[PDB]
Image (cartoon, coloured by chain):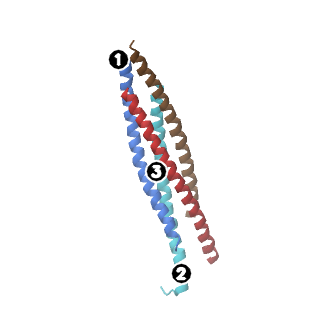
Chain colours: A cyan, B blue, C brown, D red
Amino acid sequence: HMMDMTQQEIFDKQRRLQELSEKVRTCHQEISALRKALQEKEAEMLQVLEDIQTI
Amino acid sequence: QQEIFDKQRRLQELSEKVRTCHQEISALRKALQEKEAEMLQVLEDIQTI
Amino acid sequence: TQQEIFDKQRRLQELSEKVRTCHQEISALRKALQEKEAEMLQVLEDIQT
Amino acid sequence: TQQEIFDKQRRLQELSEKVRTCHQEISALRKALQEKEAEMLQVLEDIQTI
């Protein structure tokens, strides 16, 4: 609210670092969850494929 | 042979299941690709600050 | 019976073997992709903190 | 604090490169996974096909 040019830059580093970290977390849980759902789906598909071989 | 036709029918059903699984995989994979693009964008964006 | 029945069955065994090939290759690539994803997610864990 | 704002910034650059490396590879490996699922699907089409 009364920052000078120097104080504003320090503020920006802290702030923009903070935002980036928050979005990276969001991205992390979402990628992690999708990765898992794909993993499960691939396993299911591969099992069906085993049954096709087994026939 | 009717035998060879019958097992092929069973094989049709299994293939259908495989195809369904794959359409889900393909859609989930696309969503994951969008998420990774978005994240890589957050990381490049970070730099240059 | 038919020579055709036989030939059809040669096609079907070989085709099934192509399925085995496909399954091993898909499964192994799937595991490689999973491990690499897990790795990248650890790096993201580092960035968050 | 400014010493930590420094340590943070460079670690961020290094980890970011490692992530970018990781996705360049994953993206390609996924390309391979895809064509190969394509190949198996075609095979199944052939089994069905007789």
Spatial CA distance of label 3 from label 2 is 37 Å
* Residue at the image position 44 percent from the left and 38 percent from the top: D39
Asked if badges 3 and 2 are on one and the same chain, I answer: yes
Task: Name the residue carrying label 1.
Answer: B2
Which chain does the residue under circle 3 lie in?
A
Task: Name the residue carrying label 2.
Answer: A9
Q: Secondary structure at mark 1?
A: helix
Which chain does the residue under circle 2 lie in?
A
Crowdedness near tag 1: few (<14), some (14–19) or many (≥20) residues, C-alpha within 10 Å: few
Callout 2, which amino acid?
A: Glu
Which chain does the residue under circle 1 lie in?
B
Reply above or below: C15 against D35.
above
* Residue at the image position 56 percent from the left and 45 percent from the top: C32
Query: Percent from the top left, x then y, of residue C22?
Result: 49, 35
Q: Quadrant of residue C5?
A: top left
Asked if residue B14 can be seen in this view, the reply is no
Reply above or below: C1 against D30.
above
Left or right, C11 with respect to D6, comes to left
Q: Secondary structure at mark 2?
A: helix
Callout 1, which amino acid?
A: Gln
* Residue at the image position 43 percent from the left and 40 percent from the top: D38
Task: Name the residue carrying label 3.
Answer: A34
Asked if badges 3 and 1 are on one and the same chain, I answer: no
Quadrant position of the C terminus of chain C in the picture: bottom right
Query: Percent from the top left, x then y, of residue A33?
Result: 47, 51
Quadrant position of the N terminus of chain C in the picture: top left
Query: Percent from the top left, x then y, of residue C8?
Result: 41, 21
Question: Looking at this view, is B28 or B8 the one in front?
Answer: B8
> Furthest residue to the top?
C1
Q: Tell whether label 1 touches label 2 (CB within 8 Å).
A: no
Left or right, A18 with respect to D2, comes to left
